[PDB]
Amino acid sequence: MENLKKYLEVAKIAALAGGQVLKENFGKVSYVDKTSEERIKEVILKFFPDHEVVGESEYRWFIDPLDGTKNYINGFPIFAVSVGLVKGEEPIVGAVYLPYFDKLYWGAKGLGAYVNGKRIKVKDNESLKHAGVVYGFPSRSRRDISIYLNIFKDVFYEVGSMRRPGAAAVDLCMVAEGIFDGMMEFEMKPWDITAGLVILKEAGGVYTLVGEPFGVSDIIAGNKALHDFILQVAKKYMEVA
Amino acid sequence: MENLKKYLEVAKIAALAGGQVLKENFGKVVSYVDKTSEERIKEVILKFFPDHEVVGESEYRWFIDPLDGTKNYINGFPIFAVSVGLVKGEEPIVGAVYLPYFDKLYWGAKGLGAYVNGKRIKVKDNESLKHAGVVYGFPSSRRDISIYLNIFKDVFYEVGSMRRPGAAAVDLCMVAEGIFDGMMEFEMKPWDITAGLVILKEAGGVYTLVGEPFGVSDIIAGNKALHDFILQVAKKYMEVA
Amino acid sequence: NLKKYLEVAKIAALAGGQVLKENFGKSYVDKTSEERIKEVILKFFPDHEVVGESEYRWFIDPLDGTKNYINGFPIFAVSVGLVKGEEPIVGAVYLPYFDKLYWGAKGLGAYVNGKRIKVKDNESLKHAGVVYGFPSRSRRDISIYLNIFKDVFYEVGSMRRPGAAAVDLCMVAEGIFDGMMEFEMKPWDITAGLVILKEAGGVYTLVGEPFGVSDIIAGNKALHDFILQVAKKYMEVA
Amino acid sequence: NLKKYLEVAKIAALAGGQVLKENFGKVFVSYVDKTSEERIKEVILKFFPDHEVVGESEYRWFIDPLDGTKNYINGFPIFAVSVGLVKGEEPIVGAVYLPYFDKLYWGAKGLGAYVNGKRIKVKDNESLKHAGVVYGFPSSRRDISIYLNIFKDVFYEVGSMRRPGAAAVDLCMVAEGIFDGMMEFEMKPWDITAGLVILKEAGGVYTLVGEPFGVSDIIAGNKALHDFILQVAKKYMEVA
């Protein structure tokens, strides 16, 4: 933690470096996915050769060169680059950049959560009918779809509104910014969420990780209210330990 | 209707009138906004055409949506719009939809084409389902939710991706713009889709309206491929006539 | 009908600005623009008069920054101002590229997209920023403007020539620039901007014939007094 | 190795631009400038430890942490970060970032000039009366008159003349085809080196009067305007 602030500024530059690849290529197009990754990898390693990078010790950078690929290929502006860092098992730094909006979300353990310099935080709201929730799950799941459909139906009925933007890292950043009350994505990878979670926690959010935090996981995050409720419902059709 | 041109130009201005209310109030944590936007629109339309009828909540009928995507707008999510559509008798002839946050004005008129801020648009060519992008939306409902979950899962298994942005007028413009192959909206009002529908049609899109075009309806629109696919699936779980 | 003239001015500017927006990066524009502006105005106030290249006059610039617009420089706007008798009371200046709408009305304050604005404070002249402008083929001798330019140049921190008076007035109003100096002006290029600047707590002096060819010196008290100080040394005033 | 120098350059500009970006509007200055400078110099030296950084060997980087300082402090969006690479005495790499507009101009010798992954080129001109020129000079080492005379003669011939207040950005707008040319006096290497590479690869022409790596005056634009505003200059200050 002696160079936490140096890790942060490096995470931010890495996200921007790969975010520029997404920027220059938007609307023109998978070579982008690899070019963004190389750039991110280059920045991290030149600064910290010894660290390990994961995607696709005591310092593991979990990166997502392009979160929201399908949206990116179709032209839907909800996509980003995610750059998270974890010491041992503890996630300590997060950087998520939204190229199309030129919005850079970031945060470090105990240092706060920000978006382009402005401090952010999850919103205050108990009321479920006044709440907004984003969600997401795969098309060819490892788990039966019906389960996800049943969980959806239950929250959908109590919540004020639900949205499926198509990019976990962004969903995580909008919850941390106080736009959406909570989220719930299933069958996630560490690089999909690591950076976003750090930011969410620093913005004062709560979250339950189901499964191996660095393997395949499920995530239920948001303010106190939605987290407990999405979690309650989430365990009627599946198991949590 | 020799004034199509004038009708179009008025629709656009009116959408800009209401959109201005939506943009300068965005972010300011009661929906006096919606009422004010509506007031500006009705006002513009009725100074140019005093005898035309304006619908939303007698040969020419203007269907207007002062605020498509209320939930998103309140929460701080960019996907919201204002729609202004003109119907002569029964035929939709002019459409204008404005995305204030993006300062994007989608417009079109019968036989004159579809446009977005000056550039001509059109639906995409692809007929491959696994590559297709689809947007959907059903309310939280008049009919049993199971029906929507059933139509969703099926399409979900075939298409490349599915999104729920939360504002039908925008879903229609993005389909018209060729970002999404198709859209799927259930239990709509005429002022939710009339404008976006004119636009979609001029972009070369195909669509199926279920129920009374000027009463509660369901809309399935997109390129040929997706419209044929979504419609066929829907017909397995619900009635269309 | 005070709050009503303002809403119409805003919609009129937006209407004309939309034309500029659709064609940016390509006079049909200028013509089409004023066409939309006068049309919206006369639809809401058939008794009012429109002017712009009856106790209620609207001075409009369908496209301020024509040259910038043609080159692809983002500095350009639409200007819609209203005068009652001889007093500027309502103004709207829209900048299509930045999607920023500046508006104001006597007693109601100045705004830019729903945000209230005000001119800036100045303690040191060498910290001030000034925007200026004069024509290439001018009625006055360029020597006069060069003298005015130097004197002001040596005293302030910076001087900029953006190319759109209507936009210069607005930037002084928002407190980006301490003040401006624009010479050989027409009423439709500055009326809407003046209303906005004054409601932003600004000061200004018109030289010549308002609603005619004039000069304009505007900004916070400090720069206005200084720019006017210099001007008086090389030319006519009152 | 040009390709690797260019990618690094873009990143360096972006990094320093981020500082400028998250501090724009917040009425300090030395802090932003210095913080931006430190981030740019760090990235460069990280990929090329042997290179030399300059501004305020066989491979020198001329960087401007914040071009358009006064504009930046005032809140006028015309400002940027300039990162240029020089091999020997020749400008070979250039990256100019405009944080506010989120536009990144870039180029490398023999590779072309771009803006956010968009190939750019100077505009074609015929009539001087249709030309647009950006100018600028310090408040100076030469008698203002000299510059005012040059400005005056050009002013009389072209359609328009603007003074945005940021050389780096100026050179990029000429490269993009917005302005036909620009004249700027009393320049430093870090102010124009990046823009120069970008301009030249956009098919532009420029003349450096003075010491390229010292204090200099720059005449740059397409062929037309460059020749024209070069004629006028040597009519008042006698370029070599």
Image (tube, coloured by chain):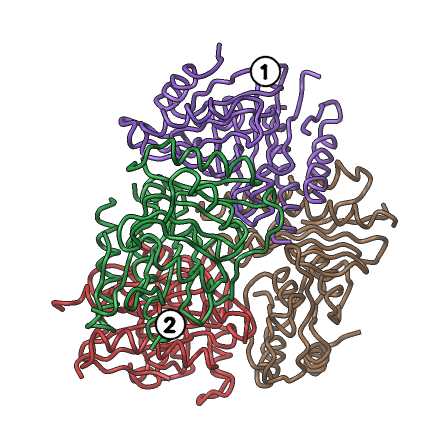
Chain colours: A red, B brown, C purple, D green
- Quarter of the picture holding the N terminus of chain C: top right
Q: Could you tell me how far apart the alpha carbons at marks 2 and 1 are, in whole angstroms?
A: 58 Å
- Residue A215 vs B47, above or below: the answer is below
Inspect this view and state whether residue A200 appears.
no
- x and y, in percent, of residue D226 in the image: 49, 50
Numbered circle sitting on residue C209: 1
Q: For the residue labelled by badge 2, is the local secondary structure a helix, a strand or a loop?
A: helix
Which residue, given by chain and number where applicable, does mark 2 sit on? A18
Inspect this view and state whether residue A177 appears.
yes
Q: Mark 1: few, some, or many residues within 10 Å (few <14, many ≥20)?
A: few
> How many numbered discs sit on the rendered protein?
2
Same chain? Circles 2 and 1: no
Tag 2 near tag 1, CB within 8 Å: no
- x and y, in percent, of residue B13 in the image: 68, 44
Q: Tell me the quarter of the picture where residue B198 sits.
A: bottom right
In the shown orientation, is residue D225 left or right of residue D41? right
Q: For the residue labelled by badge 1, is the local secondary structure a helix, a strand or a loop?
A: loop
Q: What's the amino acid at mark 1?
A: Glu
Q: Nearer the viewer, mark 2 or mark 1?
A: 1
Numbered circle sitting on residue C51: none
